[PDB]
Amino acid sequence: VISVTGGAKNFALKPRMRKIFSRLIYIAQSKGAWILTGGTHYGLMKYIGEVVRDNTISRSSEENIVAIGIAAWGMVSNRDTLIRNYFLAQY
Amino acid sequence: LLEWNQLDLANDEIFTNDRRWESADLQEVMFTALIKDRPKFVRLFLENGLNLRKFLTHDVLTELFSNHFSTLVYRNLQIAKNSYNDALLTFVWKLVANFRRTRHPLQALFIWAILQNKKELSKVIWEQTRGCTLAALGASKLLKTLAKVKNDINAAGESEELANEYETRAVELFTECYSSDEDLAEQLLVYSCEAWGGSNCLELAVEATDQHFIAQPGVQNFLSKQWYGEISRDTKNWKIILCLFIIPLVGCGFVSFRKKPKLLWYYVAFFTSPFVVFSWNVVFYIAFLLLFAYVLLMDFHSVPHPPELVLYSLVFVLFCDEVRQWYVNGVNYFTDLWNVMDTLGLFYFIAGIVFRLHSSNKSSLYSGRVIFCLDYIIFTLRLIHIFTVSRNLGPKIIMLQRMLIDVFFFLFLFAVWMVAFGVARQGILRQRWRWIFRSVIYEPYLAMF
Amino acid sequence: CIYMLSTNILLVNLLVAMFGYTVGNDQVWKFQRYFLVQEYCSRLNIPFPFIVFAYFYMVVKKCFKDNETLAWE
Amino acid sequence: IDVFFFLFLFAVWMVAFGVARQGILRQRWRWIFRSVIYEPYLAMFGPEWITIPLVCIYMLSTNILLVNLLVAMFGYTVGNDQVWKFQRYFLVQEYCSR
Amino acid sequence: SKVIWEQTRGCTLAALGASKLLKTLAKVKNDINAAGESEELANEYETR
Amino acid sequence: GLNLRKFLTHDVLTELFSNHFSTLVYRNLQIAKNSYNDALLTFVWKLV
Ligand SMILES: CC(C)CCC[C@@H](C)[C@H]1CC[C@H]2[C@@H]3CC=C4C[C@@H](OC(=O)CCC(=O)O)CC[C@]4(C)[C@H]3CC[C@]12C
Ligand SMILES: CCCCCCCCCCC
Ligand SMILES: CCCCCCCCCCC
Ligand code: NA
Ligand code: NA
Ligand code: NA
Ligand code: NA
C-alpha cells in the first residue's frame, strides 16, 4: 500500500518527477499494490490518475491498478449529482 | 526573464510551489514565447499546467499564420505548390490559405513551426500531438517537398535535415510501438484520419520515400503478413503451391492459417491470398502460353475453333487487367518500358484478330499468323520478365532495375549507330522514299545478323 | 578507324550498363520490395481469369453510384 | 546457380522462338514438337508492318537476357572470411567423412 | 541462462546447442520480437 | 554454497516446465517442431 500525500495543487511536470511517479505506478501495478491519494483533480493526484489510466490502456491484460482517492465530501465542487435518484453518477 | 531566454532563472524563481498561477494567466506569455522562438519556455509553460489545445484558438492560429509567417517561407511554399505540387502540399497550402484569410489546431501549429524550420519548437509541439508517427511522417514529407525548391539552398538543406530528423523520430517511435505490441502497432500503421490529408503512415512514408521507415522490421513483417493473407507465414511455400495444384487438399488441413473460421472460409481465405493469387496467375499464364502455342501449331484453319475463342477470352481478361492497371497508375504506367510491352502485345493481338477475321484472303491469314507468332514471343518475354523479377525479389532488385534501363539505353545507341550504318551502306552500294527508308532501316540488321 | 571508334563507344556504353548500379543499402532494396509487394497486394486479389467478374461488378457499382489506438500511441 | 538460371531463361526464349518460327515458316504432334525444340538451336548455332516489331522484340529479348547474364555476373557481390571458411569446412569434412 | 550455463559440464557443447535451438526458434514468424530476441541470444551463445 | 545439481530434482524440473513455462513459448516450440523440425528440436521437444 502506497500512501501518496504530495502537493494538492501546482505540481510541476518535470521529467524527473514524471519518471519517478511513472516508476512508482509501475511498481504498484507489478506488486499488486494500492495507491492512496486524494480524490481531487489537481496537481500530483491528476498526474497519478493520468499515469494509472495510461497503464490500464497500455496493458489491459495485466493486473488492474487500484487507485483509492480519499477526498472530503465538503470540498466536492459539482455535488448534487452524486446523490441517488443500478445508479450511475455523471460527474 | 523570457525576453532574455533565461529559463533556469525562471524555473528557480518564477515557477515555484510557493507561488500560485493559472493556465490562462500565461496565455499571452505563451504567445510571445511562440512568436519569439523560445522553445525552452514553450516547454516550461506546457509542463507548468498550460493546455495547448484550448490556447490554440482560431484567432491565435490566424495571427501566427498571417503576421508571424515569414514571407520567404511563403514564397518557397508557393514555388513548391507551383512546381512540386502533391496531395500533402495541396493540403498544407489550403490550410495556410485558410489561416491567412475537429480542426486539429495542434497539427496547424506543428505545420506552422515545421514550415519555418523551427526545429526545437517543432519538436516541442510534436511531443503534444495525438498521432505522433503520422505527424512525423507528414512533416518528413512536407520538408522533403520544401527541400526541392532551389531558390534558397540553405533553407532547402535545413528542410532536408529536419525531414531526416522527423523520419528518424517516426522510426524510433514506431519501433517502440511494435516492440510493445504487434497488433496495436499494425492498427496504428494503417490508421487514417483527415489530419494529414486523409493519408496514412505507410502512404506518407512511401510518398516521402522514407526508406528507413519502410525498411523497419515491423513494417516489413506487416507487408509479409499482407502478402500471405490469411495463410500463416510458418507454412512452407511448396505446401501452398501443392495445395494450389491440388485444390481439395486446402480443406484437409495441409495449409495452416493465421486465424480460424465452414469448409468454405478456408478456400476463400486461401484463394484471396496475394501469394496464392500471384502463383495461380503465373500458372494460368503458362497454361495460356501452352494453349497459344497449340493454337498456332495445330489449330489455324481459317476459322476460329473453340480453342481460338478460349484464347480470345483469356486475352480479353488480360486486356481488362491491363486497363485496370492503366486506370490505377495513370500516365506513370507507361514508363517501365515493360508495361508498354504488355500494352503493345495486347494491341498486336487485337490487330492479329482483325487480320484473321478477314477470311477468304491468304495474305490476311498469313499476316495474322505472323502477328500471332510475334505476340507469342512478346508474351513469353513478359513471362521471362516475371521470372526475372521474382528470382531477384530482394537485394538484387536495385541492380536488376538499373541494368534494365542501362541496357535499354545501350541498345538505343546501337540502334542509332545501325541507322547511320544503313544510311552509309545505301549511299555507298545503291544510288522511292518508302523503299529507301525500308532499305536503310532493315539493311544493317539483316547484314550483321 | 570509324569501326574502331564505334566499337569503343558502344562497348563503353555496354560496360557502363554493366557497372553503373555500383555508383551512387538494405533500406533501398527493402523500400523497392515493399513498393512491388504492396502494388501487387493492392489489387482485387481474385485468381485469373475469375477477376473479370469482379471487374464487371466494380464497374456496375461505380456506374450505379480509433481513439484507443491514438491513446495507446 | 545464376548462370544456370540465365540459361534456363534462354531456353524458354528459345522454345518461344521455335514456336514462332514453326508458326511462320511451316503450317504430327511428335514432328511438331521435335521441330519446335530443335529448330532454334540448329538455326542460331549452325512483311511491311512486321519488321519493325520484329526488331523491337529482338531488342527486348536481348535486353532481358543480357540483364539476366549481368545479374549472373554481379549477384554474388550483393548480400566475409567466416562464410568461405564455413564452406571450405563443409566441403573438406564431406570428403573426409568417406 | 548465462548463470546456469556457467555451471554446465560441457560448456562449449551447451553454448552450441543453445545457439542451434535459438536459431531454430528464431525461424518462427508468429512473434517477430521473440524471434529477434532468440536470434540475439543465439549470437551471444555462439560468441561465448 | 548451494549445490545446483542436487537442487534440480525431477519434481523441481517438472514444476518449472509445467507451471512456470510460458504458453506462448510452448506454442512457438510446437510451431517450430511442426514446421522447422530438426534432431536437436526433436530432442528438446521430447525433453519438454
Ligand atoms: C505449371 C508448372 C510448369 C509449374 C509452375 C510453377 C511456378 C509457376 C511456381 C512454383 C513455385 C512458385 C514460387 C514460390 C514462391 C515464391 C515467392 C513469393 O514471394 C516473393 O518473392 C515476394 C517478395 C518477398 O516476399 O520477398 C513470390 C512468388 C514465388 C516466386 C512463386 C512464383 C511462382 C512459382 C515459381
Ligand atoms: C571492328 C573492330 C573490333 C575489335 C574487337 C572488338 C571485341 C569486342 C568484344 C566485346 C565483348
Ligand atoms: C538483335 C540486337 C542485338 C544488339 C547487340 C547485342 C550485343 C550483346 C553483347 C553481349 C556481350
Ligand atoms: Na561495330
Ligand atoms: Na559493341
Ligand atoms: Na536474341
Ligand atoms: Na543475350
Image (cartoon, coloured by chain):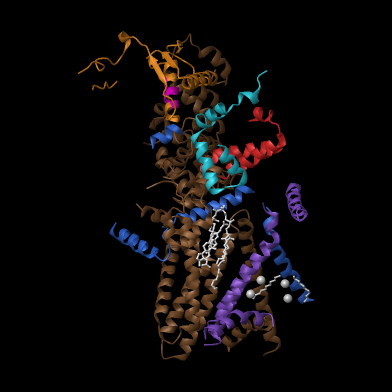
Chain colours: A orange, B brown, C blue, D purple, E red, F cyan
Which residue is found at the position 45% from the left and 51% from the top? B229
> In which quadrant of the rendered image does the N terminus of chain B lie?
top right
Is residue B139 part of the magenta span, yes or no? no
**How many marks on residues?**
0
Which residue is found at the position 54% from the left and 81% from the top? D50
On screen, residue A51 versus residue B118, left or right, reads left
Q: What segment is highlighted magenta in the picture?
A: A49-55
Q: Which residue lies furthest to the left in this view?
A: A85
On screen, residue B41 versus residue A63, left or right, reads right
Most foreground residue, E27 or B281:
E27
Q: Which residue lies furthest to the right in this view?
A: C1
Image position of B379 with respect to A18: above or below: below
**Residue C26 screen position, x and y as percent:** 62, 48
**Residue B422 screen position, x and y as percent:** 67, 81
Residue B44 shows in this picture:
yes
Image position of B233 with respect to B29: above or below: below
**Residue B12 screen position, x and y as percent:** 55, 13
Residue B70 shows in this picture:
no
Most foreground residue, E35 or F7:
F7
**Residue A67 screen position, x and y as percent:** 40, 18
